Image (cartoon, coloured by chain):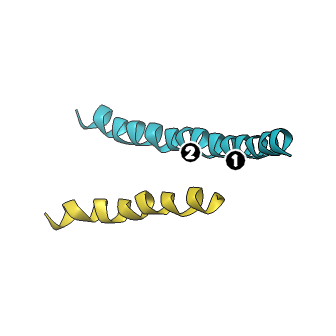
Amino acid sequence: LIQAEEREVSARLAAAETALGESDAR
Amino acid sequence: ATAIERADQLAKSAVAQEKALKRAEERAQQLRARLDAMQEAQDQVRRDHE
């Protein structure tokens, strides 16, 4: 179980970090 | 300056599009690498355990 969520939480960054740049373009 | 003005802003918007084009296309391409890697990284195990 505790193994399970960690991937999503870590991936959240990889998911989240996307939002960083493309918005910043404009 | 209606015509040429908006035309230039469309030009620049296009430019923004192409930078997006890169980032996405080669982000997919770069992900392909580890996409491959994990396969054979399991595969030598798959071959030798049996």
**Chain letter behind tag 2:** B
Of B23 and B50, nearer the camera is B23
**Which tint was used for chain B?**
cyan
Q: Amino acid at mark 2?
A: Arg
For disc 2, the marked residue is B27
Residue B31 tag number: none
Rendering coords of residue A19 (x, y %): 49, 60
Q: Residues within 10 Å of mark 1 (few under 14, many from 20)?
A: some
Rendering coords of residue B6 (x, y %): 77, 43
For disc 1, the marked residue is B16
What residue is at 27 percent from the left and 65 percent from the top?
A: A6
What residue is at 63 percent from the left and 45 percent from the top?
A: B20
- Residue most extreme to the front: B2
Disc 2 and disc 1: Cα gap in Å?
17 Å
Instruction: From the viewer's perspective, tell me whether residue A19 is left or right of residue B42.
Output: right
Q: Amino acid at mark 1?
A: Ala
In the picture, one chain is yellow; tell me its letter.
A
